[PDB]
Amino acid sequence: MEFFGESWKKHLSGEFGKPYFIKLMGFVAEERKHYTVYPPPHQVFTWTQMCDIKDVKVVILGQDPYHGPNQAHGLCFSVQRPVPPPPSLENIYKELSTDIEDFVHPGHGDLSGWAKQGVLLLNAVLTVRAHQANSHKERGWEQFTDAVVSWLNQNSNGLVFLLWGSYAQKKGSAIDRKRHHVLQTAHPSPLSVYRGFFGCRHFSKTNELLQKSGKKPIDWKEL
Ligand SMILES: O=C(O)c1cccc(/C=N/OCCO/N=C/c2cc(=O)[nH]c(=O)[nH]2)c1
Image 1 (cartoon, rainbow, N blue to C red):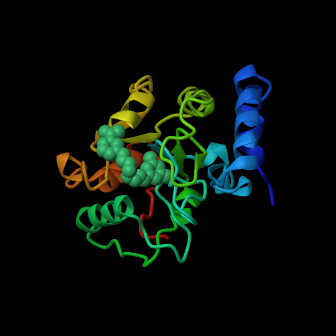
Image 2 (image 1 turned 90 degrees about the vertical axis):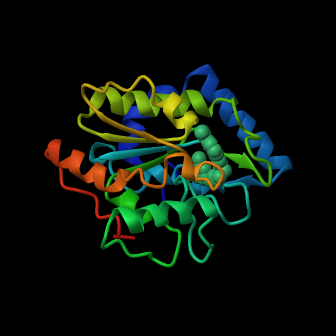
């Protein structure tokens, strides 16, 4: 089992020796000595384990990992069996059900099936102290995940970026929309879902855009 996916390591390792990155590694390591930190070390980079970097087709940008026990596992919005899907994820599934006629609810919250198809599920901040939202904010992760976004922007074409909420929209603000597709709507959390996310139909729209990029569509029910 790898800590960090091989193909991703090849293209992102230029970040590793930078002052901010060493500092970030030290911050997280010190946090883990005194607190419970999610996800566990072996799951921080799950987003690098599921597909080759060259095989990314769709990018969903999140903010903070889930901060409750057993929830975060390195893919944004996703929870491994048998953890119940959180409200945000139930909303994602609800939109899918109305957006795509034939989408079936998988009865779990594990989005590994999407990740394997090249759906990058990247949170901007990759660790969080248990029960404390945004506890690891602005400690170095943002610069690293910005580098991930910048790499994909510069080194692939016809990606579909899905930016849900103002935070994701900001993080995706410098994406080249001549070379990539960008869809924007409200965050799927209960507090914002009815301000755009329900009825956004990003999942069907994504597959149409992928065809225009000459790429095979995502099977959203393959979970
Ligand atoms: O950026 C916004 O506009 C906005 C508006 C309303 C709400 C939120 C965020 N709400 O977050 C709490 C809901 O649960 N979040 C789950 C989550 C899991 C994950 O892995 N990554 C996330 O970004 N989020 C953002």
